[PDB]
Amino acid sequence: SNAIRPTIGQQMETGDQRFGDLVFRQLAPNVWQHTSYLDMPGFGAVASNGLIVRDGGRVLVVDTAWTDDQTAQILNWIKQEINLPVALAVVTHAHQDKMGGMDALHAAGIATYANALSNQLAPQEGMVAAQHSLTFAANGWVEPATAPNFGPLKVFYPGPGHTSDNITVGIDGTDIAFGGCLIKDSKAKSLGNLGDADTEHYAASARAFGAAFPKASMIVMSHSAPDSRAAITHTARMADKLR
Ligand SMILES: CC1(C)S[C@H]([C@H](NC(=O)[C@H](N)c2ccccc2)C(=O)O)N[C@H]1C(=O)O
Ligand SMILES: [Zn+2]
Ligand SMILES: [Zn+2]
């Protein structure tokens, strides 16, 4: 198959597997990155990344693809490659790159979770809410009763940044943590779309993510390949410029 060469988002490199319209990359024996692409007319493709985690006899998903059809392709890939049921998905804020495929998850009977605030914003953002709401303590950690049977997914709300509702997820038992759209890579020159951002609190929120997962060495994010912790520090330094 031909390589997909997005205008925004990482390129395909060694270890990147094309499946239909999407790309998959194994990050750890039990963790894979899913990548889907939105074609913007006149601009080209924008890649967005999420995660797939095997936890024993079940699979957990972080973020949908941009669309329902792409998200059904993620479920197809899981069926072919892993052949275990998806127990739940957690989506990391109410924008299209992270929640555009909710209906595909629901059609498949998968339990969906998002920040309560994401669910409240979804109908205002042209999204369908997740079926369950996560809530958070004053220090950002998820209230465990709201995240039942999450296995290795450790959900952390770092504060407002890219959006007010953005959440992040550490993968316990690995050195991986997922920043979603809050974190950009260590070579990025921009924080991306700031239209819904909290420019005052962004730098502290980025740093809070790093402090929540202080031994995560592989930082996964929505629009770049997995990076070092310099993604966190560089994002925070860019965000310092917003104040
Ligand atoms: C990659 C993006 C610049 S766009 C994406 C998101 N936007 C969407 O999901 C929009 N529905 C969209 C509109 C036009 C073109 C592409 C995406 C956002 O506003 O954070 N996340 C941004 C980001 O992570 O900075
Ligand atoms: Zn967003
Ligand atoms: Zn994004």
Image (tube, rainbow, N blue to C red):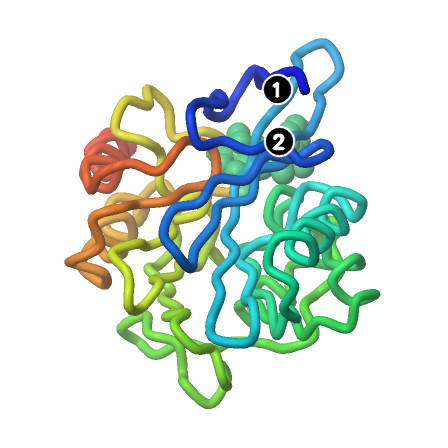
**Disc 2 to disc 1: CB gap under 8 Å:** yes
Residue 148 percent coordinates (x, y)? 50, 86
Q: Quadrant of residue 128?
A: bottom right
> Which element type, helix, strand or loop, lies under badge 2?
strand
Residue 106 is tagged as none
Residue drawn at x 38%, y 30% is 191
Residue occupied by mark 2: 18
Q: Quadrant of residue 43?
A: top right
The answer to whether residue 169 is visible is: yes
Q: Residue furthest top?
A: 42
**As displayed, is residue 163 above or below residue 24?**
below
Q: Nearer the viewer, residue 156 or 5?
A: 5
Q: What amino acid is labelled 1 in the image?
A: Ile
Disc 2 versus disc 1: nearer the observer: 2
**As displayed, is residue 9 above or below residue 51?**
above
Residue 41 percent coordinates (x, y)? 75, 15
Residue 46 percent coordinates (x, y)? 60, 25
Residue drawn at x 76%, y 51% is 72
Residue occupied by mark 1: 4
Residue drawn at x 24%, y 42% is 232
Q: Residue furthest right?
A: 107
> Which element type, helix, strand or loop, lies under badge 1?
loop
